[PDB]
Length: 463
Ligand SMILES: *Cc1cc2c(nc3c(=O)[nH]c(=O)nc-3n2C[C@H](O)[C@H](O)[C@H](O)COP(=O)(O)OP(=O)(O)OC[C@H]2O[C@@H](n3cnc4c(N)ncnc43)[C@H](O)[C@@H]2O)c(*)c1C
Ligand SMILES: *[C@@H]1O[C@H](CO)[C@@H](O)[C@H](O)[C@H]1NC(C)=O
Image 1 (tube, rainbow, N blue to C red):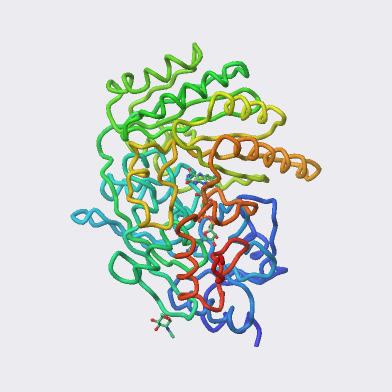
Image 2: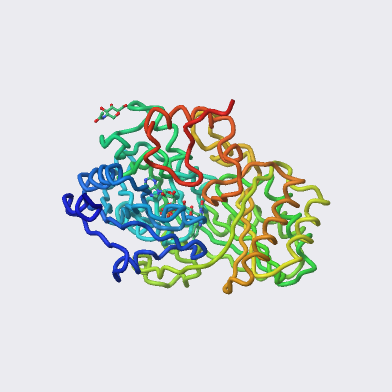
């Protein structure tokens, strides 16, 4: 019996190659690897997820879940041709528990709509990232850094419980009590490798007080060293109420952007040392806002935008290779900063973003060894993106950003951030001391390797 016949038993919506539904379902954030699946199935019930998992095993196809489809390597199209893509768009269950300070979120949510629901429900939030069309699922299962993460932790740090459909078909629950091993794995390594998460339960945080958004911007190739060095010096001492990111690109633009959980009249003592050592005359934007306005501004909407825009943020696409790396305190040496900028200036149509972690952050304050997310001792991460619009430049752009990664590598660590997924990183760079444990759990929960992609947790232990 065929896959059409098998999935038809479950009754979920499907799309199969050659139809227009299948064509539009192929949309992904990165258009570089246009993998062609066997089929798309759109579950709205746990039963139907169980059907897809059963049918893929019977027909002998691969199977990956897809949330918001932002995977930098197109792994939610399978990372290879011929997979069954289980698009979880139909799982939008929401509920807020004010007394418990928790919320239930279905694995189909995007960050934009999720922020709106949590704001309307109780002026709360989770510390998610700032791209509104990103799915909560991949985001949360790989970490998740946003502009309140230095106060409230990573998204993954706020997973209190998940429910997933495992490889043998059973609905499972994982939290600090039930199935602690699976619960460890999904907080940092949950993408695909252990089954299809159907819902999350998050710890939520009060954001009803005013907050303050700041951004200091320059357009001058000559002040890049000075601005980045000042960012590093300042970043070592930033209190947890601030989450900031630095930006830089080969056209000469650079900026510091951040969110302060506090009143604007308190902000300037906290950014004084950065501005004092950066170059003179930054473009200066400092703005007191409420939380749902902050979400809008962090995605370039005017703060007077209707909050309901967060339900209809247009999905945009790009074609790119991305890499990442972690840098430890006190940061790059001065020689490293010049090597980085010189390497950046050998090319174009790229950008570079530095998310601040640091010893004051809730991220670095987790006890190590309790989550699959290991990067608990860095000053900042580097996101390295090189784009193209014509495949002629694919090889030169891919070589450019890989040269850049190797230059920075001399002055930094070998660890990378798994939500900036990179097929050329060894898994030890993402999972390190916890990878043995991850493989043990993979053996236990999917011995047949039903759920795999080019960088799924393997079944063989390193010797
Ligand atoms: C496109 C995009 C990505 C961003 C952006 N900004 C970020 C930010 O501000 N902070 C961050 O920490 N990261 C940012 N990123 C990267 C994203 O965090 C990652 O790209 C996330 O992994 C995206 O998640 P999602 O949209 O759900 O992408 P998918 O491609 O669908 O999934 C990725 C990965 O996870 C597996 N998976 C999805 N769904 C499930 C379920 N339900 N159960 C198990 N596993 C699941 C997929 O199979 C795949 O392997 C800004 C922008 C614009
Ligand atoms: C699937 O495996 C888990 C743990 O191995 C077990 O608890 C569950 O009952 C299994 N379901 C089956 C065999 O249908």
